[PDB]
Image (cartoon, rainbow, N blue to C red; front, side, top):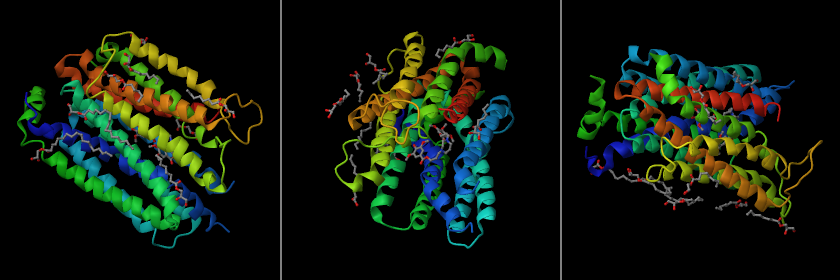
Length: 381
Ligand SMILES: COc1cc(C(=O)OCCCN2CCCN(CCCOC(=O)c3cc(OC)c(OC)c(OC)c3)CC2)cc(OC)c1OC
Ligand SMILES: CCCCCCCC/C=C\CCCCCCCC(=O)OC[C@H](O)CO
Ligand SMILES: CCCCCCCC/C=C\CCCCCCCC(=O)OC[C@H](O)CO
């Protein structure tokens, strides 16, 4: 088992980047979708876009990670991975074209929501199939996917900041997002196609030659990863983007405080947390400390809620200084990426090799169940 040059590891890293960089770029272009709806409409469509997008994203994402966990064995992995990648590529290509064509508000809203359902439907299959595949490899190769996903969040943050500072129209920034995603998806496909000729890949993928029982074996890590993202999506981004600076010296802060202090902070430390797990995985697959630290994250709900949210009707600002918010976001984000990566890395290793693929697929569903439960909870918070 010699991953010569770490080619397979790097390919798995690129696969993670590819799974989320398009969707992350889509999310960072929300301002383009809402502003486009406002300049078209003559209870509005922009006022409901975020909530309808959320519903059109989590419900498909959850349904198809669930189905994949039950049916991944009936479809070849290359069909599930390459087929999903090609579908997402086509949808983002269309998303890019719609930037340049005139279309009334309601058709644009509807067509966009349809594409959002396809992105998360094929995204579910893609992600469920990647973690299942990675379940056959050492734990470090699931961390490669998680790490690559974190970089996708980092690039998304850099793009958001650069778009604001560019001064360009939201539409031409969004068009750049979507074209970049298309190119990244194409690169991701090329990298995947290079795996079969690598001996390290064939060595663990060779091992292909009772869902209820598998679920019991990974239940601790499956439920932990679910609780990780219940908290995370519960608080981020819907709640945290409402925080305002209390030390800003210039009106130039206003448009940069959130993309910098919130989004950039989160994606930097989330990415670094995921990346650390490729080399350092304390407390280990059997330690009860891992679920315990996942539980401890509950503390971030009061902490962040009592930061400088303005306007606010009912609570007080206990932590008004920006430093509190940035610090909470860093620990909030680092604990997410690190513990989440540990859960995904360890889940498949609580089971025999012939079941590690299904274990990874189930872990993907519970990760997405956490995303969905967080969206529900955050829609009260
Ligand atoms: C497709 O699979 C995933 C989806 C999400 C995901 O979509 O999370 C959010 C869930 C609920 N959201 C619904 C969709 C829209 N969104 C609001 C979009 C506006 O947000 C952003 O601009 C944004 C920018 C970022 O970077 C600049 C982010 O970090 C990457 C980000 O994360 C949610 C959102 C609300 C929350 C997260 C994942 O791993 C972390 C996935 O991999 C399993
Ligand atoms: C903002 C920073 C961006 C972060 C960027 C990601 C960091 C990459 C991590 C580890 C490199 C390990 C990869 C080792 C290089 C392998 C290249 C390879 O594929 O080797 C075979 C090649 O095709 C024939 O020479
Ligand atoms: C804006 C400045 C932020 C950018 C800073 C770039 C830092 C590089 C990435 C993560 C650092 C955290 C520790 C990195 C350890 C990663 C382990 C690794 O990549 O090696 C995996 C290899 O394949 C073994 O199997």
